[PDB]
Length: 381
Ligand SMILES: [Ca+2]
Ligand SMILES: [Cl-]
Image (cartoon, rainbow, N blue to C red; front, side, top):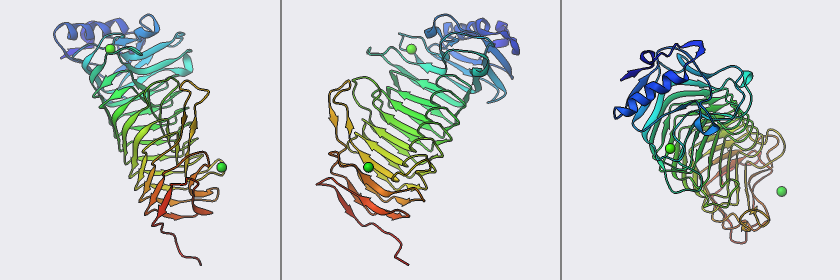
């Protein structure tokens, strides 16, 4: 057990406590590990150096703990004017293990600073073999970052990020970038200017259990390849939770495969509830998908192919083998179809046992091998 007071941290809302807190982290690390405690207070921090130096660098076996979200706050100094990749982060180009944070708030002070600031960052190095592992983040709030809220990054094995909140950030609340065997559980993302949750860059064997995303400018959740010619995300389970009142689709799956969205409540989004865009083997199971298309006419579920022939892969990604089963889909005034396929090569969809109401047509299919069975709809008046 280490206490940042013993290293000269003032926690007074004005003094720069970066050097004191980093000294407590380094002492815990040199001793073989420990928990660095921050008692209640606002702890101001400045940038440590170059963008990859963040503000504070955690190390192997070191955990930060505050007195509770909103009680312990680590906040960027007024007037900061440089890119900061993680107010708390792991070292760049090192495989860092058994570290994390709990019971505190990170505040990026976007109203009184400039340039891109991310709340949490960790990883090894883009394109390089190597992984951080056993990151545990519990009961953390990340707010007011001009960049990302939480950005666990390439590569991390066995992330646990639970019971946390990301809000009022300029990009995405939570990013899962090249995560392997990781979990987001019981998190909330709201009022971010882009996505609530963004799973990207080859993430695989990843669980999103009981997460909530609402009021974000982008998607509630997007699962996507990203901008580079990399292995697509695959083997992703979205289990339960709620994705509502977002600016774009509730849930977007783009150039990713073997993603399951199940038992979720998806409603009030600007465009479709669920969109599948150049994806294979997606399973949309047992969801309530209703009252979407709030911004303009759209189907509750859209299935379409992604034309990357002039992009980084050179490939045309048809959407194939989508299973849409056991959903209750209820359109509202702007909803066109319950499930729409574009006439773009999308094929091998199978609709099974959906309850579909409130739409112009339950299913609007084009694939020569796409099928629909067991749709339930209210009988005509
Ligand atoms: Ca690292
Ligand atoms: Cl269309």
